[PDB]
Image (cartoon, coloured by chain):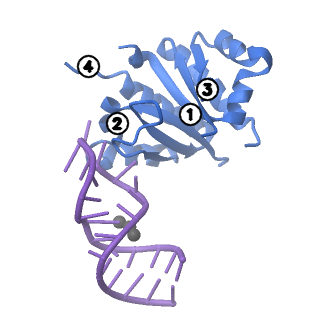
Chain colours: A blue, B purple
RNA sequence: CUCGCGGAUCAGUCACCCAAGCGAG
């Protein structure tokens, strides 16, 4: 199948639930989806964050499926707040360009399409961070549109 | 070169990748 990349950010508390004991959960997920998934090592954060990186390679549908499973795990946290309803994605600068559009018309449309709140990082690597927030179903739809833009691009 | 075994150290619900050492083409 036509393969695409999706890079998503993983809060440290969420990583163990993703990989699983012995790696059983991340292996089973790769098996079920066909996607290849690799995490950064534990203290290997994305510049400017406390978050590990998840590189996923697969069909569009696998990308979407794998993301949702990450979001489900992220939704479960309670160590003893805003981050439980966030998604963060790392996109190439050219696809961020496409996510934004002329005078920001595409991101407005993406937010109007979803019920999600979508931001990007300004211009501080040739990647930008896309932050999506809203309820689960809003975020999912937003993430679907974003993967659609990842798909629509000669990178 | 590449692959197979292996699994130092890191990690730690921590996999994949990656060291020593070994094997094969
Ligand atoms: K190996
Ligand atoms: Mg091995
Ligand atoms: Mg090896």
Please determine whether, in this image, residue A61 is positioned above or below residue A120.
below
Residue A31 location, x and y as percent?
45, 49
- Residue at the right extreme of this rendering: A102
Q: Are marks 3 and 4 on the same chain?
A: yes
Q: Are marks 3 and 2 on the same chain?
A: yes
Please give the residue where the numbered disc 3 appears in the rendered image.
A144
Q: Residue at x 77, y 42 (%)?
A: A154
Choose the circle earlier in sequence order: 3 or 2: 2
Q: Nearer the viewer, mark 3 or mark 4?
A: 4
Q: Residues within 10 Å of mark 3 (few under 14, many from 20)?
A: many
Residue B1 location, x and y as percent?
54, 77
Residue at disc 3, secondary structure: helix
Give me the C-alpha separation between circle 4 and circle 1: 25 Å
Q: Are marks 2 and 1 in contact (CB under 8 Å)?
A: no
Q: Residues within 10 Å of mark 4 (few under 14, many from 20)?
A: few
**Which chain does the numbered disc 4 sit on?**
A
**So how many labels did they put on this image?**
4
Please give the residue where the numbered disc 4 appears in the rendered image.
A78
Q: Residue at x 62, y 23 (%)?
A: A122
Q: Are marks 4 and 1 on the same chain?
A: yes
Please give the residue where the numbered disc 1 appears in the rendered image.
A90
| Quadrant housing the C terminus of chain A | top right
Choose the circle earlier in sequence order: 4 or 2: 2
**Which chain does the numbered disc 3 sit on?**
A
Residue at disc 4, secondary structure: loop
Residue B5 location, x and y as percent?
32, 73
Q: Is mark 1 within 8 Å of ligand 1?
A: no
Q: Are marks 1 and 3 in contact (CB under 8 Å)?
A: no
């Amino acid at each position: 199948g036509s393969q695409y990349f999706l890079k998503v950010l993983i809060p440290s508390y969420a990583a163990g639930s993703i990989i699983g004991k012995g790696g059983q959960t991340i292996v089973q997920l790769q098996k079920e989806t066909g996607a290849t998934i690799k995490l950064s090592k534990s203290k290997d954060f994305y510049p400017g964050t406390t978050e590990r990186v998840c590189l996923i390679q697969g069909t569009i549908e696998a990308l979407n499926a794998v993301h949702g499973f990450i979001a489900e795990k992220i939704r479960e946290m309670p160590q003893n707040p805003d981050r439980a309803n966030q998604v963060k994605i790392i996109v190439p600068n050219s696809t961020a360009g496409l996510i934004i559009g002329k005078g920001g018309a595409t991101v407005k449309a993406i937010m109007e399409q979803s019920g999600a709140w979508v931001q990007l990082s300004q211009k501080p690597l040739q990647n930008r961070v896309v932050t999506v927030s809203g309820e689960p179903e809003q975020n999912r739809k937003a993430v679907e549109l974003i993967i659609q833009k990842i798909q629509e691009d000669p990178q």
